[PDB]
Amino acid sequence: HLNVSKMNVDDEFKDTDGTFILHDLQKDQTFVYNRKRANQRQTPQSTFKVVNALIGLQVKAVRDEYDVKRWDGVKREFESWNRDHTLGSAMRESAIWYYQALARDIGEERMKTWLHTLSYGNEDISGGIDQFWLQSSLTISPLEQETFLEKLAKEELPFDKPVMKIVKRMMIQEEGDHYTLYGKTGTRLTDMGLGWFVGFIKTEHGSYVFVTNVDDSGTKAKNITVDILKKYGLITS
Ligand SMILES: [Ca+2]
Ligand SMILES: [Ca+2]
């Protein structure tokens, strides 16, 4: 019976500058490691795919998690990007080009309205409709990400219920007998110097929202998170 207020995660951040937030939804309690960094707005990277997918489905710029966009044949850095993608696979593989096409179809006026309705960070898309989340104008703090994700977990955002169910399913990372891990990585892929892993874990006793943010890659952020979630008995089997 975890009391998140009594946690310690210092060791899991060995050799890394980062922050971690865990919100126990059933008890309405939040643990924060490195509160100063938790309050620092940073560029969201591919964690923005969560918001982009919600808006895109809501406004019918994409149909469902299986909405296919054909690859243009341009060889990009990661072979996993060099194939036809859907909304869901491009989230799983962080295939930026798919979400750039989606953002263009949403369009700047609609995107700006939605980020204001959602109070998403600094709401600043001036870096360009298909660039603004990629080490660019938009920023959001780890605590602001947690506030947004709690509303998604509780289905309190201004989106249709089926839209939120689709995006949550798209976030599933791992399923055990006793838990389901949902999450999205983000990385500043130029220098690998900023990383995120944000999401939720559902157990038999309740759900938890987490945000991990680090001066390292999104893969490192995810590995730190999984280490913590195992240490505290939320990832079991
Ligand atoms: Ca440890
Ligand atoms: Ca380091």
Image (cartoon, rainbow, N blue to C red):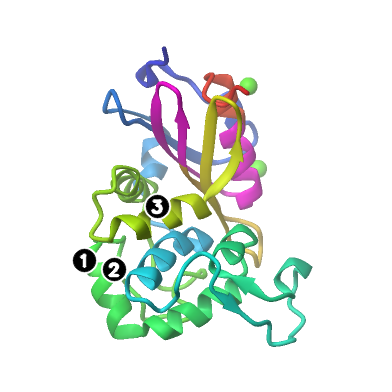
Q: Is residue 37 above or below residue 89?
A: above
* Percent coordinates x, y for residue 226 in the rendering: 60, 33
Q: Looking at the picture, tell me which residue is in the foreground, 63 or 27.
A: 63
Looking at the picture, which amino acid does disc 2 mark? Leu
- Which residue lies most toward the top here? 1
Instruction: Let me know if residue 4 is in the magenta part.
Output: no
Answer few, some or many: residues within 10 Å of disc 1's Cα (few below 14, many 20 plus, some between 14 and 19). Answer: few
Viewer-nearest of discs 1 and 3? 3
Answer few, some or many: residues within 10 Å of disc 2's Cα (few below 14, many 20 plus, some between 14 and 19). Answer: some
Distance between mark 1 and mark 3 Cα atoms: 20 Å
Which element type, helix, strand or loop, lies under badge 2?
helix
Q: Earlier in the sequence, mark 2 or mark 3?
A: 2
Viewer-nearest of discs 2 and 3? 3
Residue 177 in the figure: left or right of residue 106: right
User: In the picture, residue 56 is in which quadrant?
Assistant: bottom left
Residue named by callout 3: 165
Task: Identify the image quadrant of the N terminus.
Answer: top left
Which element type, helix, strand or loop, lies under badge 1?
helix
Q: Is residue 172 visible?
A: yes
Looking at the picture, which amino acid does disc 1 mark? Thr
Task: Identify the image quadrant of the C terminus.
Answer: top right
Q: Looking at the picture, tell me which residue is in the foreground, 108 or 167.
A: 167
Q: Is residue 120 above or below residue 97?
A: above
Identify the residue at image location x=55%, y=41%.
17
Residue named by callout 1: 117
Residue 83 in the figure: left or right of residue 164: right
**Count of numbered badges drawn on the protein:** 3
Residue named by callout 2: 115
The span shown in magenta is: 200-226
* Percent coordinates x, y for residue 216 in the rendering: 62, 49
